[PDB]
Each structure stands twice: as structure tokens, then as C-alpha cells.
Image: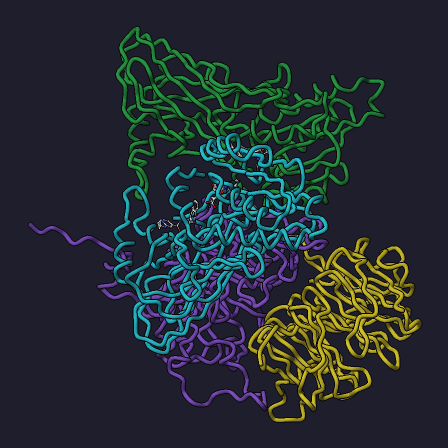
Chain colours: A green, B cyan, C yellow, D purple
Amino acid sequence: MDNLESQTYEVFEKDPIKYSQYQQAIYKCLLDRVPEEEKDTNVQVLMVLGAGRGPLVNASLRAAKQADRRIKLYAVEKNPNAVVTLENWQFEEWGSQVTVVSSDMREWVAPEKADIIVSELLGSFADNELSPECLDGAQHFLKDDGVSIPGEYTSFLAPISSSKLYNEVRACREKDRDPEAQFEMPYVVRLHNFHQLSAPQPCFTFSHPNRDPMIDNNRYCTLEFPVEVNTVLHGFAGYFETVLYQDITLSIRPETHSPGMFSWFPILFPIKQPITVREGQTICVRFWRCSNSKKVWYEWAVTAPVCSAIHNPTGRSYTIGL
Amino acid sequence: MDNLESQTYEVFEKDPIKYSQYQQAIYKCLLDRVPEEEKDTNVQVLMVLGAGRGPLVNASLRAAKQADRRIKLYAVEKNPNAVVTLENWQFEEWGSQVTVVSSDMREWVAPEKADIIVSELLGSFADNELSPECLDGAQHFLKDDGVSIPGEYTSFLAPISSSKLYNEVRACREKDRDPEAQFEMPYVVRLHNFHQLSAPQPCFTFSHPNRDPMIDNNRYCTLEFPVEVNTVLHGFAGYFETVLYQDITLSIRPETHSPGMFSWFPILFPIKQPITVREGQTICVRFWRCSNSKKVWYEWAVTAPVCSAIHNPTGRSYTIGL
Amino acid sequence: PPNAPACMERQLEAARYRSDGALLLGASSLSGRCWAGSLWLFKDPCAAPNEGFCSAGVQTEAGVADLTWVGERGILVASDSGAVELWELDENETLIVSKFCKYEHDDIVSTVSVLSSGTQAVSGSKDICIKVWDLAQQVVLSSYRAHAAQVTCVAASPHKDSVFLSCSEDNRILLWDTRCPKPASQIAPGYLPTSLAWHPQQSEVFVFGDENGTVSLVDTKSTSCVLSSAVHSQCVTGLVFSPHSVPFLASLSEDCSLAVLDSSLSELFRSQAHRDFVRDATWSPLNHSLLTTVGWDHQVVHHVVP
Amino acid sequence: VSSGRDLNCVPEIADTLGAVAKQGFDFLCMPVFHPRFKREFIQEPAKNRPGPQTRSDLLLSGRDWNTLIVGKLSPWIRPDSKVEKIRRNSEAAMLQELNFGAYLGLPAFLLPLNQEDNTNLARVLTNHIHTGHHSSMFWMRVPLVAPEDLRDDIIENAPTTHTEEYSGEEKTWMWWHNFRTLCDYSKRIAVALEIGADLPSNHVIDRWLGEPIKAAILPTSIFLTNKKGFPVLSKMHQRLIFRLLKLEVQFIITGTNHHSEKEFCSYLQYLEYLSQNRPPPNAYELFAKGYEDYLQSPLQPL
Ligand SMILES: Nc1ncnc2c1ncn2[C@@H]1O[C@H](C[C@@H](N)CC[C@H](N)C(=O)O)[C@@H](O)[C@H]1O
Ligand SMILES: Nc1ncnc2c1ncn2[C@@H]1O[C@H](C[C@@H](N)CC[C@H](N)C(=O)O)[C@@H](O)[C@H]1O
Ligand SMILES: O=C(NC[C@@H](O)[C@@H]1Cc2ccccc2CN1)c1ccnc(NC2CCC2)c1
Ligand SMILES: O=C(NC[C@@H](O)[C@@H]1Cc2ccccc2CN1)c1ccnc(NC2CCC2)c1
């Protein structure tokens, strides 16, 4: 529903590892797709779906030079303001090799099928920027044997204690809306003064392409977190891991965090009322990924040691517009 | 977004003129479409788009018996609860002649094209129940020479004075929303204690089928209302007229009101602040019909004798979900 | 050729045939990094718009909003900078040198027209002013603020040095005679006038195009537009009369088409060759059946009018 | 004196900005798309015009876009046109330019009020203000005197009115008042008051009192010339400058140099001369500085 600002693209382009990992993934994929004997006759069709101002376009070109393989590039971008940067760069630097497309990947009628679809539509909680829905509407122009980079992603959740963050969320009460709406929405936050109460556990997973006859992006997960400490539960930290290609991965999970990667901060799902947890008790949380044709949202509830209210029912406080 | 209750369908089925007018329109259309020499060989394909509990289905059958013509009926209905009534009636009374379809007319893949599409998707302000959008998604399964009943509809507006209604709208202030949202939304109301300040004037018109290369349901109208009285403007009454077929029409305009027709009450578009109007002054109002892929809404403003704020900008207070 | 740029800017603004048959081209860069302009001379019109096949070429400081021939070697330009600039073709006609660049307008110079004598010119601007220039002295003789909005078009009468027309976004069509103390005369309000063309033989007759795509025929003495036609689906950008004894009228629009009309404004020819806004039309003095058009699609199309 | 240069011609953005900064200007008002580059949004083939649609955001640093550039709406954008096709393309183009300005993080964006009916312009701007997340200022360019009322009396069959029209002479205040009423007093919408060669009567000037004037537009053509050839202002113009200096408005210089023998920064040097020669702050103003129009809740004395 919104378009990113120029300076937002600018800061994230400074990520020291995200783009070198993407380049390495494309490099490995090109060598596995076209052998040495075909290096000058086989042209691989690469599509950067959500090109931004063009850093994955440059990463794709550098990877093709590294692999000594031939590529035909498409740079698809829905943000028309970012398209200005893309079309000025295409005229001055890239040339005919890169075809710039000003369109939503779900509505674009591609002139040919792709060998490789490259995208970075991931959110802090993996699928909260609607990468499943966007890539589902784009997989029809991917070859039957075609590859999607990233191939899969998994979100992670961990219960947390933070009276400081509980107070920050509480202070988000706004006029002209439900007085508790602020507790029924996630926040992107560089978590600092908190206590992680149990090791992160995998929540939701998505794989690309999705060749199932009935595609369903809705999800329901039950997580049981052993707690070996007396504490107060205030919410859940959300992280993700992604498989770009084979062993080339990215992670924001604290235990496996990709070095120097600032492109994603964790997410925080708050709870309306703090919950007392004693040593040896288990925190049980339920998360739902819900949707209709217009929007996507999450619903969540604590069921042990005590029940909380169901948070964000029907997306009454928070939705991600399609 | 919502489905009508059983008793809502029940009361409107008691309309003494709406259905006899629809029957008369279908009757006239059948005689004009198939001559006497073809009365036993030509079967006209009729589609009731939004069949409800089936009264237009019975009106279509009675019209075919009246015209002594052959018809094949389709009763399309998106409300699955109304579909129960339709399928029980089809088994017990109609039989094979009527094919019941449980679907949205915009998503239904018809097995054959229609000669006549019959619908009653009209609101108090004609197009406020999204008849243009619904019939636009349904016209692809209408023959190149096919007829739509209704063929056209026009909304009407009239400035009104009512301190009583102004107070009723004012009392609609709700918690957990903008304190003036109640003035930025229309209301269906049987207007009684009011003063119509100028004769109703046509606002927006839609025609079916719409064979234009670029279909645009968005609208912008400027209306100038001569006022020959000292008064206070509180809002605008909305009415409509529809051409079912040729001279067979329906109207809720007070001057041409269809007798006994209670199926539509007028609509009221309020204004946040009452406006003083002196004898001989002109009330100038601007109305916009706006949309995106998810919703439709109206925006309105008074520009003479004084300007009001633009009401309902971006549909912040009121939208009709697609 | 030397001093000529290796690349011509995409947006072709003007095309003017010289009496000998040489083609003058005006272009602007209306997008990308640099918003400048260029002037081109093509002794072979079929070679246009290829830079390697031009007779002469030069880069201007800013975009070319309009241009006109000043005799056989002079080129008068309406610039985005607010300048009216005179460029002169050298002795060997292989270079285009600047004679003057005078910044007298406070906004974009949108239109220029050389007066009948060829010694004076009229410029119109977004700054709402109309100026009368002395080309030899390189100065402004008179400055007129008659309009109330941007001047869209200025057209010098074919044979009277003191008579010209102007039209603007203020919805006025003004008939000028600089021999009067109040030089302008307004000739029911409707759609905005966007283009003007004096009839080449009937000294008191002119045509005007509007923002709604309508072309109208007017007689200054009668002051009535009894003859009109809905020619285009969009704004009439330009109106150019053919060099014939009984002239044809070319009308160019933002609907990307070119139309050729007769004396009663009836269509004889319609061309959809352009894939973007048709900006100018020039009839060949050598072959009267040939009409050349330029567009924002960088196309130089040669039409055979029946 | 916080001052800006207004330009409608920018061949190279870095060269132009460097040139205006050298002259002493703190900011530049410029088009974000080429002012003559009319764009089609609905009908083919012009709708499918290959890009780029304007120049790149990469041409300037983030800091420069946020502090030195004031955007300007293209002159062909007419959302209140009598032609339906022009109204629709103008709405789409206005949203495009406004969103490009939001994309660049421009501190302000100039839009004109040059006619009585700006209803659809108000509606499109209100829609933009209530869409997405941005906090840019909208400066409505409005003249003290309408061009129709300051035109030279040179139309033989359309003479200028010689009889006084008290309310008629304040018509541009009503254009502003109506626009801001439609936009429901948005704190993001302010006035860019354009001064002309002939100042109107005092009552016309006084209508602007209490209005949110953020900028004052000074065309080079309003400046008189002294014995030394330097640009100056009449005593009446100077009086208005001192009134606007108390409101701490940003001064904008528009038009070309009309004192060609002198350097361009001379128009700016005259403004700082006026600013340096204004009355010094008295004892009251020394303490009251910074409290102007700042609302304070009265104390509970007991
Ligand atoms: N459905 C969509 N169709 C096309 N582009 C999209 C879509 N959804 C998101 N985008 C764009 O995808 C980009 C997502 C960014 N996270 C990535 C930017 C850039 N490729 C980078 O790695 O820095 C943004 O520029 C979005 O505007
Ligand atoms: N897009 C749609 N597709 C299918 N049915 C629809 C759609 N929109 C509305 N309807 C149905 O159309 C009917 C509209 C009613 N006003 C008419 C009911 C009935 N035909 C009558 O005349 O009493 C309702 O039953 C709606 O559920
Ligand atoms: O998680 C974040 N935002 C969403 C996330 O999905 C983000 C969104 C985005 C948007 C455009 C381009 C790339 C990306 C990268 N992915 C985020 C937000 C704010 N600041 C961050 N890091 C700071 C900047 C200095 C350290 C991170
Ligand atoms: O205008 C009305 N409602 C919308 C209108 O579009 C309505 C909606 C509807 C819904 C289902 C079937 C038919 C219809 C007919 N069209 C309306 C609402 C309430 N009461 C009404 N009349 C009373 C009942 C006793 C007199 C009228």
C-alpha cells in the first residue's frame, strides 16, 4: 500500500553481507544450471522481482561475471519513484542487458519465462512483508525447472520479559481508536533491555516455487517454551532464517545471526496483560497467519501457564494490505 | 462484505410494484428479441444476477408465460444462506428450467452466454450498492447483442434543511473513532421532518452494458441549486431513477416516485457544520465517486454560499468494500 | 560535423523547411540527467534524425520550446531559460553560431514569431508577457502585459509588420495592431485556445485550435467562428497551412495524430505514425504533396498527402 | 534572512545548485519533473512513453534533498480544468509529483492558487495528506493582486475597471481561505505570498494578517534602480518587507536579472541590508523572544 522513501533504500544498500550472500547464491545457481561446454550458447533469464533502486541487479551481473555465464536481466519494481533510479541507471550504465519493468509482480505479463527469480521481500518475521503472496503471483512466469532465490524461509519466536518494552507499547495508546489496539500489533524494534526466556523455536515456513494443487498461505502453530526461571512474560520476539540457495543462507536468529547484517531488526508481538511465569513452567503460545483477498494478518494467544485474550482477532488492530 | 438476513429478503419481497415492473420489462424484452414465428424454436438464456431467495426468478418465469416465449434460467447468488432457499425451491418447484449458481457474478465462469441479464443491485443513491462494479464483471458472459435489465440508472441530489436530522447525526458520535466521522458518511433514512431547499438534480449516471474501451466508474459532479428562501443547509437528500427497459422504469425521486414502492428509502449525506443560506443565493455542491481495487466511496463539499471541508477524504470515515 | 553533438535529444520540438528545402530541427531533453537542447540542419530531410548525416548541429544551454527561421541563415529560439536567442548559420552552412542570447522573460519562452518584414519578432512567455524585438539592435522595443495567464501562442500576420495574434490560458484570443494606443482587441467563454494560424491568402482570416481538440475558422472583421470541427480527441498543438494556391491545413495533437483538412475543415488525410505527441509539421517547398512531422517519440515522418 | 531562489529552468541540477549557493541562497525552488514534459496516464500510445520520467534521486545527497530543495508543481497540471481528460491526467500527474517529492524527502512543495476554483486541487492534495507516511509542507503560491487585476490597460474592447471594488480587490485572500477551508485547516498547508510591482490598498494587505505565511515571493521586476545601478525597493515595498521580517518568512527571489550590469546576488544583498537596518529588539522583546504564538495553559494559582 505504501512506497519506500529514497533514503530508506539508501541505508539498506549499505548492508555488508546481504548482497554478497545474494551474489554467492546466484553464482552457485548459474554453475549448477549451465555447464562449461554451454557457457557461450546458453543465456539464463534472470528476473529481479522487487528491484528497488537496483542493488540485486548489480549483484546478479557481478555473479554472472564470477560464474563466467550469460544472463538476460529483468528488473521488476512496483515503486514508480524507485523506477526513476532504475531507468536512469539502465540508460547510463546497464544498457540492453537489463530490461526495467514498472509493475507489480502479481500483475506483470512477462514476455518470456525465467530460469531464476531473485527477490528480497522478507520481513523481520519472514513472511510479514507478504513474500508468499507476491511470489505466488509471480511463479507462473518461472520455468517448470526454474529456481527461486530465496528457496525457503522460516520465522522464529521466543518469549521475552521486558517491563521497559511493555511500558513503551502501553505509551502507544492513540486517540480515535480502541484503547488497547497498540498491544494487538507487532513492532519492528532493536530489542535491547530484555530477557529471552526460552530458546527461539520455528513458527512458520514457506517454500518457493509452491507446486501444490491447492496453495494455502494460512498457518496455525502451537509452541511450548520450557522456562527454567521465575519471570514475567511481556511478549514474543520474532526472527527469521532464509535459505537463499543450498548452503547460502541469511539469519536474524540471535544464535545464527548473519555478521554485520542490519537489514532486519527483530519483531515484537506484545500481550495486553503481563503474565507471571514460575521456574519449571511451560509458556504455550498459539500463532495464526490469516488472510482474505484484500489483506493478511496474525492472531496470537498464550494458553499456558494462563490464557490471554486472543490478540488481533479478524485483524481489527493490524493488517498488511494486499 | 456482509450477507443479508432472511427477514430482510422477506420484507422487500412484499414490494407491490418493484417485481411487476421487472416482469413487465422482461416481457417487453422477450417480444422484441424473439418473433412469433420463432416462439417454439428460440430459447432465450436469462441470468438473474443476485437472485436472493428467488423473486426475480418467479418474475422471469411469469414474464415468459405472458410473452409466450421459451427461456433457460440461471439464478446466481453470492449469499450462501439465500442459496439454501433457492436450491430447496429449485428441487420442489422450478426443476431443470432453473440452474442455481452459488457464486459472485464477478468470479462465475458461465457455461454459455446470456441473451438477458436481470439484476436488482441498486442502492438508494443508485450505484452505492456497487451495481456498476458487479455488472462490469458480469458483462463478459452477456452476448454481443445481449440486454441488461436495468439498462441505466441515475442518482439525484437535493439540498435539505433539518435541525432534527442534524441532531440525530450529531448523536451518532462513537468511542474508538474520529469525533466527526458520523458527518462523513451517508445514512438510509425515511426523511420526514425536513425542508427540501431546491428541486432534485441528476448527479451520476451508469449504463449497462458498458462497451467503452476504458471503463471508468469514478465520477465528478458540480451541482448549482437555486434557493428562493432564507434557511440553514444541513445535508443532501439522495434519490435515484432507473430505466429497467425502454419505458419501464422505477423511481424514488419525490416528483416521480413509483407508487407503493418502499424497497428504497432516501439517502442522507450530512455536512459537519450547518450553512446559512439567504433568499436568492445558490448552493453549490461537488460530489466525487472514488475507488481503488478494494473499495468504493464518495467525497463531497459545499463551495457556495460558503465552503465546507471536503467530506470523507480517501474514504477515511466511509467505504463500500469490493 | 565539428561542434555538433554525437547524440540528439529524444524530444523533437520543431521542424521547419527552408525555401531551398533544407530541414531545421529543434530538440530538447525533457527527462534524464541533463535538460538541455539542440539545433539541427539537414540538407537531406530523409537522413533526419540521424546525427551522422546532418549538415550542421549545435547544443543550446537549455531546452528549445519553439523556433523560427529568420530569413535563410537566421534561427530564432524560444528557450526554457527565459531567453530569446538568435543563432546564425555560417558562410559554409556547416556551423551554427550564437548572435544574441537576451534574458528578458521571467519564465519559459513558449512561443516566437518573426514579423512580415523579417527584421522584428514577437515572443510569448509563461511570465504572461508579450515582447516585440528589434533583431538588428538585439533589444526589446515594447513589453506588453495584456494577458492574465501564460501565453500559449503568438502568430505574426503574413503581410503586416504591426499585426499579430496571441492566445492564452486566460481564454483570450487577442488581435494586435501596434499602431494603436491600446494595441490589443479581444476577438461567450469556452475551451482554452492552444494554437493559431493566419490564412496564407485571406489577410483577415485565421484558424485556432483548442484544448478540447476542436479547430475553428475565424474572420477578424466579422468576429464570428461559424465554421468549426471536432478533429482531435485531445489538445490541438499546432496548425500549419500548406503552400498550395488553395491551401490544405495540417492539425497536430497530443492524441499523437496528424490530420489534413480542406477549406470547409473536412478531413482528407489522417496519420497515426507517431507513438507520442506530434509537436510540429512543415510542408516541403520543393514537393507540395510532402508534409514532414516531428514527435516526442524521436520520429521524423514524411507524409504523402493526396 | 533565510532566502531562496526560484527557477523554472534547471539544465544540470548540481551545477545550478552550486551556482545559487555561491550567490548566497539557502535553498532552491525548482521543478521535480521537466515543466514542459506533459505526461499521459490513460490513452495509448502516449501512456506507454518509455522512461525515465524524470532525473534520478542519486544526483544529490539525502541531506541536499531534505534541506536545499523546494519542489514545484508542473504548470500544465490543471485539476480544475473544464476538460474531463485534462482533470483526470492532472490528478494522476499531481499525485505522481507529490509522491516523488515525498520519495525525496523535500522540506516543502510549491503549488499555485491562480484562479477562483481550486476545489479538485484541494481534494487531490487532501487525499495525498491522508495517504502514506510523510511530513512535507505545502506552500500555496498566491499573489496579493490577481494577474487579471494588474494587467496593462491595452485591450481596446476590454477596459480595466477604474471604479473601486473593496471586496473584489481582496479576491486572492478568498482563493486562499476557500482552499484551506476545503483542506480543513491542515497544519501542513501554508502561504507563499507573491508580491507585485504595484502594492494594493492597505485593506488588501491586512487580509493576510493572522495567515500562516511561510514564504514571500519577490520577483526581480518589482525592484527599482538607484543612481549606482543597484536594485532597490520603493518605501511602500520596504514597509511590507519589515512587516514580513517580523513574521520570519523565507524570502524567495523569482525571475531573471533585470540589472544586467550588476551581479545577481545584489537583489539578495539589498534584502540583508533591509534586515540589518530593521529596529533592534526592545527590553520586552528580549524576554518575549521564542514565546510568539506559543499556547500556555494558565496556572492554577491556589
Ligand atoms: N508485489 C510487488 N511487485 C513488485 N515489486 C514489489 C512488490 N512487493 C514489493 N516490491 C518491491 O520490492 C522491494 C523490496 C525490498 N525489500 C528490496 C529492495 C532491493 N531489491 C534490495 O535488496 O535492497 C521494494 O522496492 C518494493 O517496492
Ligand atoms: N457480486 C454479486 N454476485 C452475486 N450476487 C450478488 C452480488 N452482489 C450482490 N448480490 C446479491 O444480489 C441481491 C441484491 C438484492 N437487492 C436483490 C434480491 C432479490 N433479487 C430481489 O429483487 O428481492 C442480494 O441477494 C445479494 O446477495
Ligand atoms: O527491519 C527493519 N525493517 C524492515 C525490513 O524488512 C527491511 C525493509 C527494507 C526496505 C527496503 C530495502 C531493504 C529492506 C531490508 N529489510 C529495520 C527498520 C529500521 N531500521 C533497521 N535497521 C537500522 C538502519 C540502520 C540499522 C531495520
Ligand atoms: O433503502 C433501504 N435499503 C437499501 C435498499 O437498497 C434495499 C436493499 C434490499 C436488500 C434485499 C432485497 C431488496 C432490497 C431493496 N433495496 C431501506 C432500508 C430499510 N427499510 C426500508 N424500507 C422499509 C421496510 C418497510 C419499509 C428501505
Position in image of residue B76 (x %, y %): 55, 38
Q: Is residue C160 left or right of residue B134?
A: right
Q: Residue furthest right?
A: C286
Position in image of residue C185 (x %, y %): 62, 87
Q: Residue furthest left?
A: D302
Residue name at image x 53 percent, y 65 percent: D80
**Residue C54 against residue B20 in the figure, above or below:** below
Total numbered labels: 0
Residue name at image x 58 percent, y 71 percent: D257
Q: Is residue D93 visible?
A: no
Q: Is residue B25 visible?
A: yes
Position in image of residue B223 (x %, y %): 46, 67
Front-most of residues A315 and C185: A315
Q: Is residue D202 left or right of residue C304?
A: left
Q: Residue furthest top?
A: A280
Front-most of residues A194 and D43: D43
Residue name at image x 63 percent, y 68 percent: C108
Front-most of residues B84 and D160: B84
Q: Is residue D48 left or right of residue C2?
A: left
